[PDB]
Amino acid sequence: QNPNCNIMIFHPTKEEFNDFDKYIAYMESQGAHRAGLAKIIPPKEWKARETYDNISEILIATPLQQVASGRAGVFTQYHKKAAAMTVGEYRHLANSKKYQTPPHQNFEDLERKYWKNRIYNSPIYGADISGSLFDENTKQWNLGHLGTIQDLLEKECGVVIEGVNTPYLYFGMWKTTFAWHTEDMDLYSINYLHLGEPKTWYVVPPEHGQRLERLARELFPGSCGAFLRHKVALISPTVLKENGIPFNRITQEAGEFMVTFPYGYHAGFNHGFNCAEAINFATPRWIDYGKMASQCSCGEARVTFSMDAFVRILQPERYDLWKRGQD
Ligand code: NI
Ligand SMILES: [Zn+2]
């Protein structure tokens, strides 16, 4: 299935939108994971929340200034602190003359601009906010409550990691950026754009993630032995074509879901003011990637959690063998 590793787009029926797990698995029987990313479009009736009133007076306690440096499509990005603000103020700042989305004829134009001018006017990302905009009544694809095996982490261990097993909110503006990464422990991620302007994703198929690693070692020489876990690298598509790294690019509109799959390297940016919600999740398929996830050796990035419970409970036949691989 899916021989060209293309980003597949699904339009589940209402019935198919009932069991989250079961549809993930169906997307995989059609080969979605081979691209490392898929778009899902919710049924017409489905809604995340009745209305987005009073999201104005919500508090972004610690927004981040994203300072890039480098050029010719290759940058390290670093995060610096900036003042607290309401979303009202952020919306307003993100539409001001300094941060607003530049005039552009089409996508190719916008992209050219983002990658040419990255180091200027460092944008402020309202990122990593612990919360959710989903209605409790929303029972299909509600990111607070997916009901996947990732929940084994909290029931077995009492282990809660923010943005991993509880959701994060992302208030974006033009040029706000996510560096090249696979998710923590190479988990799946799912992201819902709640509102506003689009988000662009670039994605490398899992089959080739190593090529991407290999390349990042040349572009940032002197580098854990798993550099990309720092999530500091920006690399433009031109630079990927130049070096023969397969990738795809897709632009997410408001109202749409993206799911990244284990070991699917991805990065991208926002086109303007927007608000996104995301969480990680897991399936039985992920366990083996979990146990395999290459961790940062220098300390700069976290070994997020222990695979122990997952193997013990869900792979009981292989558990003894897995322990002997340890200490
Ligand atoms: Ni991600
Ligand atoms: Zn490291």
Image (spheres, rainbow, N blue to C red):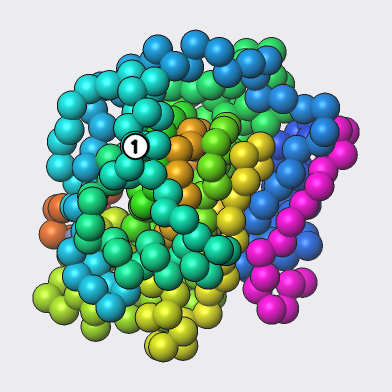
User: The residue tagged with tag 1: helix, strand or loop?
Assistant: loop
Where does label 1 land, which residue? Answer: 96
Say whether residue 148 is left or right of residue 55: right
Asked where in the image residue 210 lies, by quadrant, the reply is bottom left
**Position above or below: 12 against 206:** above
Residue 7 in which image quadrant = bottom right
Above or below: residue 180 compared with residue 57: below
Residue nearer the viewer, 215 or 252: 252
Viewer-nearest residue: 41 or 291: 41
Image: 259 above or below 244: above
- Residue type at tag 1: Ser
- Is residue 32 a member of the stretch shown in magenta? no
Magenta segment, which residues? Answer: 1-15
Question: Could you tell me which residue is drawn at 52 percent across and 49 percent down?
Answer: 199
Give the left or right position of residue 310, taking residue 308 as reference.
right
Query: Could one spot residue 163 in this view of the protein?
Result: no
From the image, which quarter does the N terminus lie in?
bottom right
Residue at x-position 71% and y-position 47%? 40
Q: Position of residue 287 (x, y in %)?
A: 51, 51
